Image (cartoon, coloured by chain):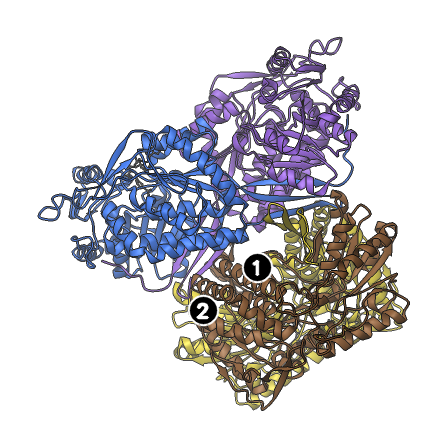
Chain colours: A purple, B blue, C brown, D yellow
Amino acid sequence: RMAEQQLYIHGKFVAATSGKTFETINPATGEVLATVQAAGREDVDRAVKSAQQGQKVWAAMSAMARSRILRKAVDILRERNDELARLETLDTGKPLSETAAVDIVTGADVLEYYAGLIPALEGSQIPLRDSSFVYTRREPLGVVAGIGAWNYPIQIALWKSAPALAAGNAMIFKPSEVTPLTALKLAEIYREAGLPDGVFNVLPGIGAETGQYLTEHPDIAKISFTGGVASGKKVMANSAASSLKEVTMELGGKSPLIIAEDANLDLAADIAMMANFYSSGQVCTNGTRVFVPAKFKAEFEHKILERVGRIRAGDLFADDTNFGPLVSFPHRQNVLRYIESGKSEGARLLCGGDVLKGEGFDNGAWVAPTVFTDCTDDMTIVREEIFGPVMSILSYDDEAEVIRRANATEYGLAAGVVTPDLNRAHRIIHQLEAGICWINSWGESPAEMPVGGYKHSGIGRENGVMTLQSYTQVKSIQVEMGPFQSIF
Amino acid sequence: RMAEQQLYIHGKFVAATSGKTFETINPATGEVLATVQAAGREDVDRAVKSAQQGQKVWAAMSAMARSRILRKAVDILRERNDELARLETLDTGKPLSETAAVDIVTGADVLEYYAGLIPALEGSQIPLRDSSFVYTRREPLGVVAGIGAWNYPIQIALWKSAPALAAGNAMIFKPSEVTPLTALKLAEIYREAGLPDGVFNVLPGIGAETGQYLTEHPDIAKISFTGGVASGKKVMANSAASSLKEVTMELGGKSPLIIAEDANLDLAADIAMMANFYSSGQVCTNGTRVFVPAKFKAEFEHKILERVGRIRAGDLFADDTNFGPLVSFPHRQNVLRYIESGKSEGARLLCGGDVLKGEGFDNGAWVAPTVFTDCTDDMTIVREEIFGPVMSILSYDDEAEVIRRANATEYGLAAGVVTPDLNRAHRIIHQLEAGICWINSWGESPAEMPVGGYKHSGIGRENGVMTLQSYTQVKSIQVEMGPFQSIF
Amino acid sequence: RMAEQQLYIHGKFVAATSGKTFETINPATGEVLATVQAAGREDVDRAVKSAQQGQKVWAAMSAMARSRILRKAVDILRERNDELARLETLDTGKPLSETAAVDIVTGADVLEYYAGLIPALEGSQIPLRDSSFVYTRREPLGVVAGIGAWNYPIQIALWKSAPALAAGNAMIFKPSEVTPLTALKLAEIYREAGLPDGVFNVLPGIGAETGQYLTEHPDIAKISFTGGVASGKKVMANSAASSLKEVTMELGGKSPLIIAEDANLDLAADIAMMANFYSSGQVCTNGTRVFVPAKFKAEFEHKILERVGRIRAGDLFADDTNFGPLVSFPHRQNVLRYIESGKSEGARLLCGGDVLKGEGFDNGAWVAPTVFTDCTDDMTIVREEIFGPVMSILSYDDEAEVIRRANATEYGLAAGVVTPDLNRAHRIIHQLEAGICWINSWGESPAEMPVGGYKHSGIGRENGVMTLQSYTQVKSIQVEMGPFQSIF
Amino acid sequence: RMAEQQLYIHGKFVAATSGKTFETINPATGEVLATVQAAGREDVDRAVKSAQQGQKVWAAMSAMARSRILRKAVDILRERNDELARLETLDTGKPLSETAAVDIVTGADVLEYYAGLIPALEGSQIPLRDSSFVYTRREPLGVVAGIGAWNYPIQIALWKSAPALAAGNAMIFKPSEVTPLTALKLAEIYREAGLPDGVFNVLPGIGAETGQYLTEHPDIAKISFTGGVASGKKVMANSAASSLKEVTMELGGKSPLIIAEDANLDLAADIAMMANFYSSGQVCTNGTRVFVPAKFKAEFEHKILERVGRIRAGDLFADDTNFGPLVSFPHRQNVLRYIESGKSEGARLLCGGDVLKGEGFDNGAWVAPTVFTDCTDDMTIVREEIFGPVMSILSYDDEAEVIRRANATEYGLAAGVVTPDLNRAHRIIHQLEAGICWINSWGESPAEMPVGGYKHSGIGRENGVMTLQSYTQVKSIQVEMGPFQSIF
Ligand SMILES: NC(=O)C1=CN([C@@H]2O[C@H](COP(=O)(O)OP(=O)(O)OC[C@H]3O[C@@H](n4cnc5c(N)ncnc54)[C@H](OP(=O)(O)O)[C@@H]3O)[C@@H](O)[C@H]2O)C=CC1
Ligand SMILES: NC(=O)C1=CN([C@@H]2O[C@H](COP(=O)(O)OP(=O)(O)OC[C@H]3O[C@@H](n4cnc5c(N)ncnc54)[C@H](OP(=O)(O)O)[C@@H]3O)[C@@H](O)[C@H]2O)C=CC1
C-alpha cells in the first residue's frame, strides 16, 4: 500500500475535514493501492479561497515569469517521466510501454506549448473615429475547476491545467476516484517549479459529492469536464443552477473509420487496430465503427484476426506487453454486458468476447480483444460507446451511403478515412460531422491542434491557441475623448 | 388594429397548428395591436426541418454570395428605418426619438458589419513534419436558435441573426410575447433580400411553451438567449438536459458608474442621466449604482435634479418626447415594489417614485423618473436589477474602497469611470469586473466591440469578430502522408 | 478617334503641364485609338498634394463610411462591365470573351472583398504589468503609388487601389503607356461612387519619366509595381535613392507545370492549354515550362496539337473568338526573337512559330499559338520569360529530378502539379519554390488568396487579408502609469 | 590584448582568405582590444553554402525541437550576462551599469520570446466552394543576412537572429567593424545550445567589402539592416540590383519629446534626461528635440541643468558611473562638428560643448553632456541626427503648432508626450508620425512590441509576432477537386 492520501491545498498536503475516504484498486491484481481522503463542502470552500489568493499573485507576475515557471514544471515532468509512468500503470492498468511513451510525454508537450504562448496573448485595439477608440483585454476568469476522467489521468490533468494556468487562472482539479494518485504528484511538481501556493489545488473525492460541490460553488467561473454523456449533463445542469459558469466538455463518442474502395487493406487493418485496441480500447476518440467495402470485407476480417493474434497481454511492466486489463472491475462488467448484447442481437463474434483466463489474469480486470462483424446501424454495440476493446465492422456499398451512416449518430468526436486518392480524402472528410479527422492515420493529437466534439460529444475545445483564449474573458474598453452628448 | 399575425416558416407566413394565440398591446394606450399565433411543439419541429433544408442551400453558396444577400437586407432596413421604428414604438412604448435613431440603425450596423466579414472567415494550417500537416475548417453549427427580449426587439433579432447567418447557419428566432411584431417584419425583409427559404424562421409564442420547445429540440445546435437571470438559468438547464447545446446568454446586471473626484460634475451628471433613464430605464447595461465622492455628493444631487426636470414624457411620436412608459403593467408593478423597498429601507427619495397620472398616462404603464440617494450596499434597490427608471446614488471616500464595492456583486455586465486623468481612468477600469467598460461616456456599442457579462451577467459575447467565429465549430484535419506504424 | 485623354487629378480631368503626349494603338488594326497626355514632374507633385488633401478626408471617415463608398464603386463596375470590357479589348487586343468575363469581374471581386474587411482592420493591446500596457494602431501610409502593366490594365488598377484605399490611403496610379484608357474610366467611377477628390488620381505617361518621377517623390510612402524584372530593379533602386519607400513588386516568372506519371492526359492537356494560351500567353503566372514523363510525352504532344487546332482567332468582339493579337507590335518582335532562338537551339517546333496572315490579320500584332518540345534546361526559351503564346514541353524521368529542375530558376511566381494521388500532390507542392501553387487546375486567383513571387519573381504579396495590412504601418504606443525612474 | 579573432563558419572558428584584418579599439583608452579577420568575397560564398546546408537541417526539425534549442541559448546568455556585458563595455565604451542591465538582458528577452512562439507560426485555410479550398504555408526564406551597428552590438545580433532562426532560417551576421567581439561570442553560445552548424555564421569585416558582398549575394533571400540613413540607402540599392531581396531597415531619427502645459516639470526633465544621455546619446530612439511650452521653458532649463550636473563620468566598470565615452574617435569628431554648427548658427549653448579633459579622459573619446536651447527648426543640430549627447530645447506656444513641428521632418522613428491628461495624451500621440510612441516614459522596448520607423527612419519592423511572420514567405495552395474546364 501507500500512506493515506490527503488533499493538496495551497502548496501543501492537508487533511480533509469530511471524515470520508475511498480506495483505489490496482486493476491488474485487485489489491488496494491506497486509501484516499475525500474533499467535503468545507474543504472545497477552503480550496476556492486558497485559489483566489494564489491567482492574484500569479496574475500579477509578468507573462514571461509565468512562462518560466511552467517550463520548469515541464523539465521536472521529463525527468520524472518513468517514475510517474509506473504509478500511472499501477493505478490504471495501462501497460508501461504506453504510459512511459504517451501519458506524461504528451501531457508535458501541451504544458510546454502553452508556456511559450503566454507572451503572445493579446487584446485588440479598434479606432472608431478621431475622438474615440476601443481596446480589449483578455483577463483571467479567476478560479476555474477541472474534473478529470480515469483513462488518461495525468494527461487530462495537464491538458486542463496548462491552458488554465497559462491564461492567468488558478485551477481546482478533481481526479476520478478510480485514478486519483498522479494528480497529487502533479500538484507537488507544480509547487516545486515555483507555482504560487493555491494556483493548482487537487481535491480527490466522489463525483456525487466532491464533484458536485465544485460545480455548485458560487466563486468558480468555469468548469472543464471530461467523462461520459450522462455525467456531463448532470454537470452542465448544476453549473447553470448555482452560478452561471462557462463550461467545456469532452464526452467521448462512437467515431467512424471509413475504409475507401481503393485503400490498401494492410494499412487499413493497422489503422483499425490502433483505433480500437490501444489502452485496451479505453480512448474517447477510438474508431469503433469500422466501415469496410462489401468487396473487401472477408479479406479485411482475415487481416484483423491476423493482427489480433499479435496482441500481447501480460506483465504490465514487461517491454513487450502492449495490452492491459480495464481500469476497474465494475467497468469490465459494463463492457461484458455490451459484448453479450452484441451476441444477443446477432452480431457475428469474430474473436474474443470473453474475459482472459489463467495464471496472471484471473485476478485482473481483463477482457479479451473483441471483434464483431456483420454489424448493423441499429445494434446497441454500434450505437453506444462501450469504452472497451470491442471493434464493430460494418459493410457498405457506396460513398454517399457511408457518409450518411457515419453521421447518423448523436456523437461527433472523431472520424477517419483511409484512401490514397486526393479528391476522395478531402471530399469525404469535409462531409463528416466530427471535430477530429484523420486521413490515413489515427490518434495523433498535437498540442497545436484543437480537439473536441460535435453534437453530444462535447462543448468547446482543448489544445491549440483558441483554448488559451477560451480561458480568458474579454473586457472591452471605450475611451471617449470627445464631449459626451446627453439627450436630457 | 393589425391583421392576425402568423408564424414565419420557410419563406412564407403559415398558420400555427397549436390552436393557441396571444395578444400584444400598445403599452402607451392599452389598445390591442394584434392577435398573434403561438408556435406549438409541432410548429417548432417543422421550423427545424425547414431550417435544416435551407441551411444546406445557404452554406453551399459562396461567401461573397452570402455577403451580397445580407447587404441587400441592410439596404432595405435603411430605407424602411422610420417605418420599422414606428412599429417598434407602438409595440414597446419606447419614444420614436429613440427607435428611429438607435434600434434599426444599430441593428443594421451589426448586420452590415458581419456581411463584410464572411469572406475573411478562415481556418488554419499547422505543419507537423515534412510528411504530415493539419488544417482546420470553421464549419457552420447547423440550426441555431435565438430567444429575444422585449426592450430592443428588432436590434436583438439583428444582433443574434447577423453573425449566425454570416457564419453559414440557419436561425429560428422566438421574440418575446410582449413584442413579436418587428421580428416578423425582419423575416419578410430577409426573404426580399434573397435569403433562402428556411434560413430565418420566426416562431412567436410564450417562453414556457415555444421557448422551451426550442431549447429541448434535439437538432438545434446552439441557443442564444437575452433576458433575466432567473429565466437564463432555466434555459441553461433545459438546453443541457435534452441535447447538449452551445448556449450564449446576456442577462443584465447592476453596473457601476464611478465618478472621480476630479471629474467635471456637469459631464458626470450627463453620463449618469444617459446611464439610467434611456428607454425609460429598460436597458441591461444601465449604470444604476452611481458612485460619487462624498465631498461632491450634494452638488451632484442638485445637478441630477435639474436634469431630471428636463425629462419629457408625452406623445411617443413627438420629436421632443424622450421618455416613455414601461413595456407592461406587470413590469411597472415590479419596478414600483423596488421603489417601495427603497423607501422602507431608509434610502432618501430625491425625486420621482410614483406612477404618472392624467390624460395620456392613465392607460399606460408610466413611472416617473426616480432617484434615490444616501444608499448603502445592503439595500435591495442597490443589489438587484430593477430594469426601470431608478438611479441609486452612493457616496464613497477612496479609490480602493470604490473598486471593492463596485465589484462586490454577482453581476458583471458593464461599468464606467468619469475622470480626466490618464492614470486614474485606465488604472480603475483595469480592476473592474465587467465585460463592457466606458471611460467618460456610456452606452455606445460599436459593431466591432465584443460585449457581454462577467460572472452571473452572461456566457459568451455578442458582436466583434469573435462572435462570428463563435457561430462556427472547429474541425481539425490531419493529413498523414508517411507510412502509418501500428504497435500490434 | 477618341478625344485626347487628359490626366485625372483631384476629381476632374486636367491638362498635363508637361507639354508632352503619347499614342496608344489598337493592336488588332494598328490604328491610333487615342492621343494621351503624359504627366511631368510638376504633374506628379500636383497629384501628391491633391492626394495628401484627399487622404486626410478619406481617413477621417468611419470605416463603414469607407466600405460603403467602395461597395458603390463595385455596383457601378458590375453595371458597366460590358462597356468597360469593350474598351479593354480595343486597348489590349484581348478577346471580348475574356475581358467581359474576367478583367472587370475579378477586379471588382477584389474591391468588393476589401470593402467588407475595412471594419475588421484592428490593432493590438499588450499588457506589460499592472502599471503599464501597450496598444498598436494600424495607420495609413498616406500617399502610395501604383504602377500597372499592360496585360490586365483595369484588373491591376483595381487590385492595387482596392487594398490601398481600403486601408485609408490615397493612391496615384500610373497605367502602362500601352494601355492607359480603362484606368481613366476607373477614376471617373470612383468619384461617382463618392470617393473624396484626390484619393485616386491617375497619371498616364511613360515609364522613363512619369514612373520614375513617382518613385523619386519624397512624399510617397510606398510603390506597388507590376511588370518585368529589368524594370523592377530600376524601380527599387530609384525608390531607395530618393526616399526610403516600402516597395511591393510582382515581376512575372517561368512557372513550372508538373504532370505526374498517374495523371489523366486529357486533364493535363486542358490545364497546359489554359496555363499557356489564355490572354494569348500574356499572363505572369503562365506555366510555360511543362514537365511531362518521358513515357507519356508522345501522347501528350498529340493531345496538345488537338487542342491548339481548335483555338479560334478572329474578330475580338465575336462570341467564339478565344485568341487575340499581342498587345503591341514591339512586343511581337520580342516574342518572335525568342521563338527564333528556340529554333536555332535545337528545340523541335510542334506548331505555330510565325505570325498569322490574311485579311483581318495582316494589320494586327498576331502570333500563332506556338509549342516547342524536346526542350532542355539550358535553352533560352526555357530560362527566360517570353510573355507570349509559347509553350515549352520538357521530358523527365524521376520525381526528385523534376523538383530540382522546376526549382532551378531565379524566378518563383507560380507552379502546379497534376495528379490524383493524395501524397504526391501535397508532397511535390510543398517542395516547389513558388508563392502560387495549383493542384489539378491553373489560373484561379481568389481575392482571399495571397499571391506573389519567391526569389526574383517579386517582393510582398497582393490579395488576402495580409495585403490590406501591408498598406498600413504599425504605431506602437506604451502607456506608463507608474513612476518613471531616471538613473541621472 | 586578446587573440586574433577569426571568422565563425559552420560551427567553428576558421581563418579568413581575404588576407585582411582590422583592429577594434577600447574607446576609453585608445588601446587595441584585438586584431580581427575580415571576410572576403570567397569567405562570404563559403558562409552561404554553410548556411544553406545548416538551414535544411534546422527547418526539418520539429517546431518544439527548435524552440528548446533557442531556450538553451537563453539559459547560457543569462548565466554569462556579466561576462558578456564586460566585453561589450570594453568594445563599445558603454558603462557596465548599462551593459549588464540592458544589452544582454533585453537581447535574451527577445530570443526567449520568439523561442516560445515557434509552435504558433501557422498558415491559413480558405474554403472557396464544396469542391475546392485553399491553404497557405509560412515557409522559411532560407538564408538571410543581418548587418549590425556599433551602439548595441549583441542586442542587435539577438534581435535580428532570434526571429530569423525561430522562423526556420539560417542567418549570416556581419557586426560593425567598430564592435565585432560579442557577435563572435554569440555564435559559440548558439553552437553550445545545439544550433546546427551553419545556422548562425558570423563574418567580421568592413561595410564596403564584407557588408556589400552580403547585400549582393544571389542566394541570400533577405537583408536586415541597422545603421544610418546614408548607408541604408546604399544597402537598399545593392539588394535590388543583385537579386530582388526583402529588406528591413532601422535607420535612426530625430525623435520629438512633447512636454505638455500640464506636465510636472521634474518628470519631464527626468524623461528628457533618459531620452538624451543614455549610452552617451548614441541611441536611435533618443528624444533629441525637446519641445517645452514657452511659459515653462526657463524653469525646465533650470531642472535639466541640475540633472546634467549629477551625471557621473568615470571608470566604466564602477557601479556609480552612468556616462561613457563615444564609441570611437572619428565619431566624436563628427559629434563635435555638429556642436560647432549649433554655436555658429546662434543656438545658445546651455552646458557642455567640449571634450572631457584630465586624468582618465585624455585617452578616451569623451564628449561632455551638451544642451542647446533657444533652438529653431532650420538649425542643423535640430534637423540632423547627431548620435551624441546633445539635447535641443525648442519653445512652442500651442498644441497644433507643436504637432506640426514635431512631424515636419523626414525622420519618423520615435516620439513621446508628457501629460497627466487622458485626452491630451492619446490625442497628441495619434497625430504624431512615428512608429514608437511613449506616454510619460521613454526607451522601454518590450519584446512583444513592434518597433520601427515611419518615413526615412526605416522599412519594416522588429520584435512582436509580426516580425516572426516577416521572416517567412507565404505559399498559397489551391486544391481543385472539381472538373477543370478549359475554354480551348
Ligand atoms: N438583459 C436584458 O436585456 C433583459 C433583462 N430582463 C430582466 O428580466 C426581468 C424579468 O422580466 P421577464 O420579462 O420575466 O424576463 P424573461 O427573461 O423571462 O424574458 C426574456 C425572454 O425569455 C423568454 N423565456 C421565458 N421563460 C422561458 C423559458 N422557460 N424557456 C425559454 N424562453 C423563456 C421570454 O419569453 P416570453 O417573454 O414570451 O414569455 C422572453 O422571450 C426584468 O425585470 C429584467 O430585470 C428582461 C428583459 C431584458
Ligand atoms: N539607427 C542606429 O541604431 C544607428 C545609426 N547610426 C547613424 O549612422 C551614422 C554614421 O555612422 P556609421 O558607423 O558610418 O554608420 P553605418 O550605417 O555606415 O554603419 C552601420 C552598419 O552598416 C555597415 N555598412 C556600411 N556601409 C555598408 C555597405 N555599403 N554595405 C553594407 N553594409 C554597410 C557598417 O559596416 P562597418 O561599420 O563595419 O563599416 C555597419 O555594420 C551615425 O553617426 C548615426 O547617425 C549609426 C549606428 C547606429
Q: Which residue is labeled 1 in the image?
A: D449
Q: Which residue is labeled 2 in the image?
A: C193
Q: Amino acid at mark 2?
A: Ala
Residue C120 seen by the camera: yes
The picture quadrant for ligand 1 comes to top left
* Lateral position of residue B413 relative to residue A230, left or right: left
Quarter of the picture containing the C terminus of chain D is: bottom right
Q: Amino acid at mark 1?
A: Met
> Observer-nearest residue: D262 or A469?
A469
Helix, strand or loop status at disc 2: helix
Residue D30 seen by the camera: no
In the rendered image, which quarter is residue C236 located in?
A: bottom right
- In whole angstroms, how far apart are the C-alphas of marks 1 and 2? 39 Å
Chain of the residue where label 1 is placed in the rendered structure: D
* Lateral position of residue A257 relative to residue B161, left or right: right
Residue for point 58% across, 26% down: A149
Query: Does residue A403 lie above or below B303 as drawn?
Result: above
Query: Does residue A98 lie above or below B335 as drawn?
Result: above
